[PDB]
Amino acid sequence: SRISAINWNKIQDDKDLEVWNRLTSNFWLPEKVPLSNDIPAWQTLSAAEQQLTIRVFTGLTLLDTIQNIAGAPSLMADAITPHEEAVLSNISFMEAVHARSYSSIFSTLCQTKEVDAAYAWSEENPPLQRKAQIILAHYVSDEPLKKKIASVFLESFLFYSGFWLPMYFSSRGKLTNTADLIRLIIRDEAVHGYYIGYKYQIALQKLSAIEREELKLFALDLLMELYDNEIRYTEALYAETGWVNDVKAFLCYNANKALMNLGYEALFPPEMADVNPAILAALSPN
Amino acid sequence: KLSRISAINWNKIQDDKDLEVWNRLTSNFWLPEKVPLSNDIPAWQTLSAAEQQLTIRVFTGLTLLDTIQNIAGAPSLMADAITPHEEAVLSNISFMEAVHARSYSSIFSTLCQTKEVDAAYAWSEENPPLQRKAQIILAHYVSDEPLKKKIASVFLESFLFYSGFWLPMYFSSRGKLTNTADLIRLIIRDEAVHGYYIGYKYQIALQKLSAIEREELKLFALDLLMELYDNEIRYTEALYAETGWVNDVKAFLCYNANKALMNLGYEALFPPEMADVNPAILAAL
């Protein structure tokens, strides 16, 4: 028995139709955002701030390119309902839109030499290569639940973390339209992690207690590995700024969200995940 | 990073047509919800029990093909992309295939009866022709013959598919089911670009092969087209049996088989005498 025609009037899990409706309904393209209105704001940023922004965004671009190419697609083979497969094909597509959005921003605000140098930086940056390597290794592996754990960490932790910068600038009245575009990405990202995290939880109920325990420990070890590598990434990128400690706190905040999307309890105490209300205000994240 | 996957750069297009198609397909985004299907409810009851059943089975068969294209087709063409932008384009195509398929359940929900719909599904799960065409195309998508996969997908989209759109487009000319006709038009606006683009990439791949290999593929194409053609003929003679339009369809099958070959860069296989179709039908497409 091959493939059967999909019946959307035979939903097997109401969650599938809900996410499908939310994701498709929230469709958008970078051309829909008035990025050109940030050109003046861009001009008020220091040379150091401009480089920082470009490198950060190139980093996010790498992550979504992977999610578009290997991430979302590697989960489609593990879907437990035909409707899930359709939703995953929408997620994969939107990851392409997300990756494409950064080029939109580069075309509108930056100079070619400046952007090309950033792409060269991303090719050699240690922490960025390592994080891409780690996740990608799980995506090509044989263990489905580990692919989902990696995917949620990529979306609810690694990604969100890069959103601090546009959100900070926006709180200062700079790059407000780019910030709007990032909130469009977050609106998708929040649902992606939630959904994939939910499917992970269901798969867990079908396993022995010994097996759930092995995955829980795996989850925490992978998180600490990605977390500490993200701290190093952060300390090098924001070396100047004076914003390193704010970003770190943001990392812990999102790591807790990644964990709960997986069905686990928050791991970082409030004293480590205290995000400036200005960032939270201007945010609208998970 | 390193030599692994690199961040995609849309300001360094490697083939202008990748950007063109990306913009056209994303610009044409749509969902079945955007179509006032309900406005077709009245006209729907003006059809006999035979017509309704026929229609529902045609749409079920089409639903089977898109589901395949969404999960197996488009996705298998991924590994064969020759530019990063093509990969992103194929992911959009794969997504829209899910929208196409989902659209049919919308039509059933808005105009049919549960028992009546589940009837078509059981039918497709055993209809000899349908299961065979699905078996043929799907066998290629699973293999490691990149160019054959492209030939197969072009046949699945520019030939196998359009062959079912005839019916809905007739009602359009007549006056019945006008909103469903708008929907089908949206699916066609996508389908036409899909065959064109993939046929385009197929031709790029051909120039890189030896002269003997191109002839080999060129022959393989005709051998696959005919096998699906006769299997399609058997499919048409059955469903449209009653009605008395089988001839109209047999003539439509040939029309789209020539257009599918053109997407691959080949010459027409059926002379205009066999691939002729009512001007009204064509005027709706």
Image (cartoon, coloured by chain):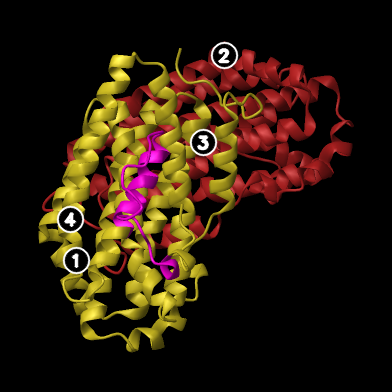
Chain colours: A yellow, B red
Pointers 2 and 4 within a single chain: no
> Residue A258 in magenta?
yes
Q: Which mark is residue A46?
A: none
Q: Kindly report which numbered mark, 2 or 4, lies closer to the viewer in this rendering.
A: 4
Classify residue B145 as left or right of residue A17. left
Q: Kindly report which numbered mark, 2 or 1, lies closer to the viewer in this rendering.
A: 1
Chain of the residue under label 1: A
Q: Residues within 10 Å of mark 1 (few under 14, many from 20)?
A: many
Amino acid type of the residue tagged 2 in the rendering: Glu
Amino acid type of the residue tagged 4 in the rendering: Leu
Q: Quadrant of residue A103?
A: bottom left
Taking depth in this image into account, of A230 and B275 the one nearest to the observer is: A230
Q: Are marks 2 and 1 in contact (CB under 8 Å)?
A: no
- Which numbered disc, 3 or 2, marks the residue that appears first in the sequence? 2
Residue A118 lies, with reference to residue B194, above or below; the image says below
The structure residue drawn at horizontal position 59% and vertical position 35%, both measured from the top left corner, is: A17
Q: Secondary structure at mark 3?
A: helix
Taking depth in this image into account, of A166 and A31 the one nearest to the observer is: A166
Q: Which mark is residue B125?
A: 2
Query: What range is drawn magenta here?
Result: A250-279
Q: Which mark is residue B159?
A: 3
- Which numbered disc, 4 or 1, marks the residue that appears first in the sequence? 1
Amino acid type of the residue tagged 3 in the rendering: Phe
Provide the residue designation for mark 4.
A128
Chain of the residue under label 4: A
Q: In the rendering, at what x and y percent does residue A15 appear?
A: 56, 33
Amino acid type of the residue tagged 1 in the rendering: Tyr
The structure residue drawn at horizontal position 52% and vertical position 45%, both measured from the top left corner, is: B191
Provide the residue designation for mark 1.
A119
Pointers 1 and 3 within a single chain: no
